[PDB]
Length: 165
Image (cartoon, rainbow, N blue to C red; front, side):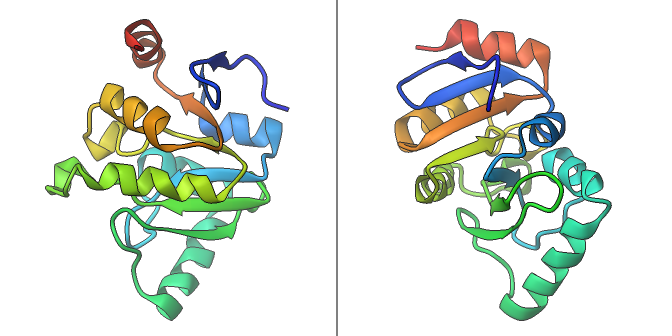
């Protein structure tokens, strides 16, 4: 199971960890990917998860997009977790750097409620440009299922825990 997570609320847990390494160790039922609408897994969590799958995630994703078209900002799709998890829940948080509406972050986190337990990153954080403190607050106020948050950056992890209300 998940180990070394700090409990923030009844259902939200957090750890300073690389989500790729966490996924390979735990092999969760669901790993969340910080996806974009095109499922183009170039950088950040998406690039890292995809690289760990030897690009199998990107090949599967391109077939999904060819069939279904792009996701909506705030939306998600369930695909294979490959060698990382049973499933990957690709969730599109708003990219503040691309001028996307930050109010869609709550809609993005609502996707997590369809799964009893998830290994996840903070949506819209990192290269998506939103304030990770705000993302954690939206997470705890939106997600009701059990979410294990992996925060790659040690200094950000310390700031998130120490500033948590």
